[PDB]
Length: 103
Length: 219
Length: 212
Ligand SMILES: CCCC[N+](CCCC)(CCCC)CCCC
Ligand SMILES: [K+]
Ligand SMILES: [K+]
Ligand SMILES: [K+]
Ligand SMILES: [K+]
Image 1 (spheres, helix red, strand yellow):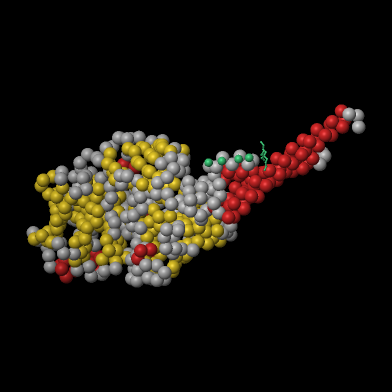
Image 2: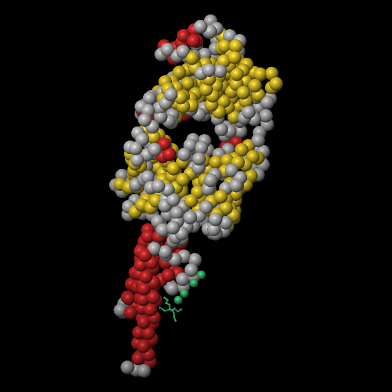
């Protein structure tokens, strides 16, 4: 196993952990604030997916500070992971193209 | 098995405090939220607050004067509600419910009747109710059980330790001179009595007393 | 906060007929509504979750419908066991809020009371007291008038009464009238009677007993 495929795999498992912990921590911080809709785990898990994937949507979002900090973590972990996979596809393509040129 | 277990009753002097319990069993997850609901006699359900025992954060109803403080001993799977500075307005039943973090209250406890009063606790006096000597019995017969002079509510009146449930009327209590009083009715077939015994089990949780009384015919 | 309006508060229906409760939220809450049943002196029990999803243990006659703001809990063929209070509860926004509650009421066939008079107990007389108990069991409608007589003359002092809610076994009502005296007052009177006047019988149904 290379590096760009170990990291791509590791980032996926790390992202799932961010999605799950983000769902749990979102409900923890959103409950107590009036009007908050991010207060059940199943839909928070759906929100964390919307959030990590940056679809966002708008049916769910945090209204508390610590809920919005949890958001920031979920977004960055999502953008970085899906970007680390792209960077891994480039190394795979740049690599196999060197083999197509002999070198 | 009974999932949420609450005491029967608590008697609180005006201005005093009380710490209600709610021991849990069954599947306890980390997503468990324990809620407390207040129900005044004759009125509806009122949400008080919620507690996440796997972390210890408590939220409370913003719209009411905060009279509670929720805790949780994670080792004993017990949620505690600490009420303090109580008046008669706080005298009600207090249920606890378990939410799986998905919005609904899957199970409730039996509730604890919190009576805010100055009167002393009085155990109940149980008296048989056998028919008069000149009462022609039809195919049925109605026996009774008189629970008088007790404080505070409630009382659990079962017949033959619960085996007999058909044809039972337990009337609401009436308050007088700081003492409650009610009676229970049981209607068994006339042939089945007194060959087969009949006994009312009256339990007053506010005094930790439970007494029997067999309904025999009059001497 | 979200307001859960339940109108009407009382709902009459004949046995075997279909009933429907109403719950309205002040704003749209999707399907995040749940229904609970509470009989007399019992804990609430979840009937329907998320507007229409059912629960195991709840009979199939309990159904739910509605989304957004208008929600409906319906019962095909109401039974005497269904006599209880029905609350709706939302979990769309924090905090969770409840409905005001709707009481179900069955209109059964008329029934006459079964009167039973009971002398005081010799155990009670030992403690210096006498209480004559009279049961008015399983009648419908709930309107009833008890009358106490002692040696022919009407009695009204020391009489406390108690009415039950609509019994959930047969949709009837019941009432207990307790005449309480001392042993002195009890031992200087002969006959004690209990008269029940009901819509079902123009002549009152009476029960008497003599202490001698
Ligand atoms: C032109 C913006 C494209 C948006 N991206 C890429 C998704 C393309 C379908 C979202 C990250 C998705 C994890 C990257 C921007 C990140 C700030
Ligand atoms: K985007
Ligand atoms: K977007
Ligand atoms: K959007
Ligand atoms: K939008």
